[PDB]
Amino acid sequence: AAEKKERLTKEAAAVAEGKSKQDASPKPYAVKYGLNHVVALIENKKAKLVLIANDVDPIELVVFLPALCKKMGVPYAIVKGKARLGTLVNQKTSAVAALTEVRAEDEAALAKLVSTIDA
RNA sequence: CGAAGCCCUCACGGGCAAUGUGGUGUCAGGGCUACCUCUCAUCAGCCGACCGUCUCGACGAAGUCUCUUGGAACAGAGCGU
Image: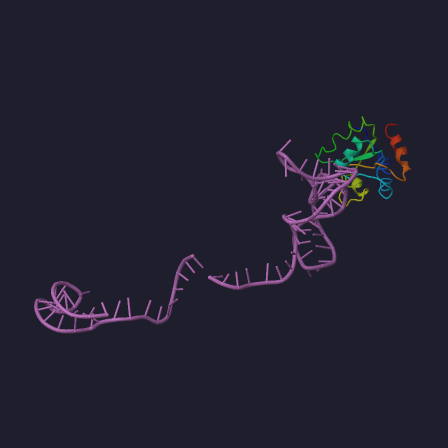
């Protein structure tokens, strides 16, 4: 798909950007965990942004995140490193999956970043 | 529902696990909502016995009487337990 630059990947993992503000929103309020829960939020538009790891396995769990993000109209970003977005949510283990329903606090950098993607 | 979970270790500590441990649930059910009733089931844990098929072992009654045959009576006939 689109290629992220390792600059955007900083700022918000949930947003097009890479994780940073994404740690915010857990401390502030709202997030998701894995693919399963994250998928639900898109379904019932709750998440502003959700992220996806680039690596992925052949998991193809994250296979229908796009198209089923772009219907709902939920912007979602690519991060590199499943671990990277795994760590921002408080998770010892990495997760290919996504997030931020509410985007507390960073209703700011988040959404600014979304603009960067799909500029 | 979403880490509330599991394994190893006395512990310390380590490992697994959101690519989902665990809870719920599985064609009579459950959940959620609004009520009625009640818990007596289930599940976790505590304490914690009585009595008593297979094999082995102990103790254990009453003739070693007569005659005949015989190498030998455990035989025949007689008497008795």
